[PDB]
Image (tube, rainbow over all chains, first blue to last red; front, side, top):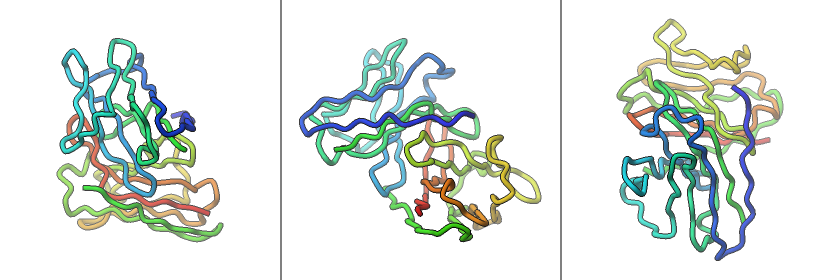
Length: 111
Length: 110
């Protein structure tokens, strides 16, 4: 499989951010999720597709109202309103396919 | 559930072993290492496999420098003769239904 570049986004505090993932090549939407990796930590499952109008469900424990998603037939996009230093890290969009996950997109959010 | 990566600083030629535990694994068939080269999307690297070696490297990663130590306790990733292009972050995770759970990872830096 071909190596893919992270999108590198340099943001200021208070900026609003969108990190992109495409529905285009998704086989099973139920298996699709974003992963958040704080620097020097193991990545964590962050939010997944959900069969609702909003289209997503955050992992348990996670409440930060600043995070949401734009989910439709084309997009599985991750949004932050009023970004701050704590948000910094790498975010990966991946779809589970049998024994493994395949990541189709990722963004490094930095200040 | 939040875990720190092991940080390892190496020079060219050094041998490395990056650890992952079997202890809490539910389905070994869904267990794999993922390699993320710096600035790149993570990639499936090697998975558990029922065999004498106990693993199978992904199509793009058949370098003889890579191996694993797999037993009832260990799911450890080895590189002999590391090089700068091996630099990045390696994550060990098990697929559980709709998502993957990563239990350990190492940052390999030069």
